[PDB]
Length: 289
Ligand SMILES: CC(C)Nc1ccc2nnc([C@@H](C)c3c[nH]c4ncccc34)n2n1
Image (cartoon, rainbow, N blue to C red; front, side):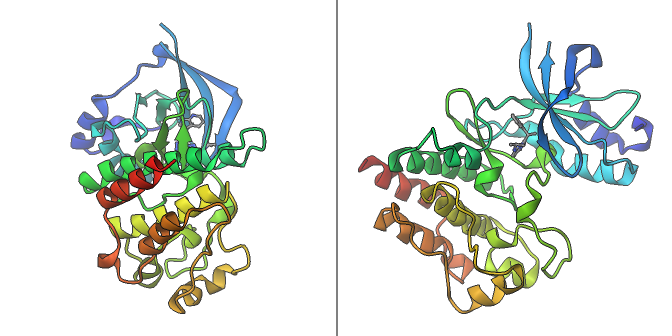
């Protein structure tokens, strides 16, 4: 039960730009389509009926935490790009934490999509998906927005097979707990096997550490969703990288694309490509297919 009067008025105004009235939203609480730490995701209908995904934040009961989460995520309403998940709105009600309403992604998350044996995406398909992610990240980087959890599990595919960079802003959560570990300097659950070396060392995230994560995402694509470093313990990821060791080239990964991956994992952040450069390089590789 969250009272608006307790929240910062500036934040309230920002939220009121995208409010959805309860009478306009039907949530199917018997139809769970995702599970996060802050709450589940449910099938919903937004009223003319629009199929949507409704993200619950009910596990966040403290007003300080609700305020922080909304403050960090509301900028989402200001983003608009074909490869970035949009916000439909926020449903405020008398009982319960705010519901976040997002576009429904018919084809689910990118990792499960490519792992699906009936799909059997080709190398061209997979590089195409990677190019789409690069374009979405190019946009976010241009807004000076650092994602911090880029991974194949956190991108989604809509009905037209357009890839949306997701799991950020008001949609931020941990949707697969297997890949987050507290074995890091912050003590919080972090995606350590997607993190840049300097993030593991300094606890800081930048666009250049997003580039590192993107390289891991490319590797995930080329392996059709294999888990990275299955043979490296979470205790050992930092030293593994310090020794200069990196993910190995996937069997069906083109040599030039592996070169792109290696560039993304340069130990010096400033030496890694920008997302603009990545779009250019991957577009050329894609075009050979
Ligand atoms: C498979 C699902 C649970 N994974 C993800 C990954 C990232 C992400 N970012 N937002 C969401 C949810 C809120 C979501 C938005 N649209 C959806 N369409 C279908 C299923 C889940 C969502 N996720 N979900």
